[PDB]
Length: 90
Image 1 (cartoon, rainbow, N blue to C red):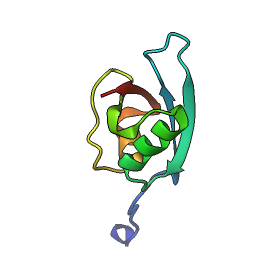
Image 2 (cartoon, rainbow, N blue to C red):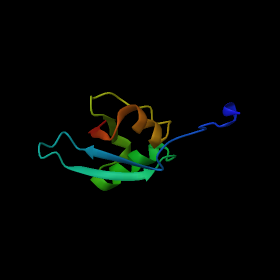
Image 3 (cartoon, rainbow, N blue to C red):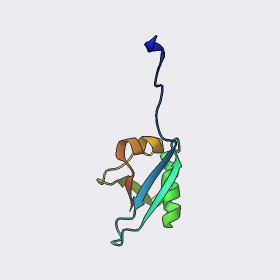
């Protein structure tokens, strides 16, 4: 019967973030894409590499300026915060 048809999961396999270095008034950005299951620590590592800044002294925050727990997936960050993120010194 109809109870036997279930939407078990839904998502998007490729997650894209537009990460802006907002301390620089030219607002340099990178659009980075990663698998949905990518640990967010690896997104910070990728972004720091592309911006040529040390991952250890950098952080990624939401467009609204709030911190993100790194121990979650890229897909979950996108679900909560959308695509626009900022890279800042920590």
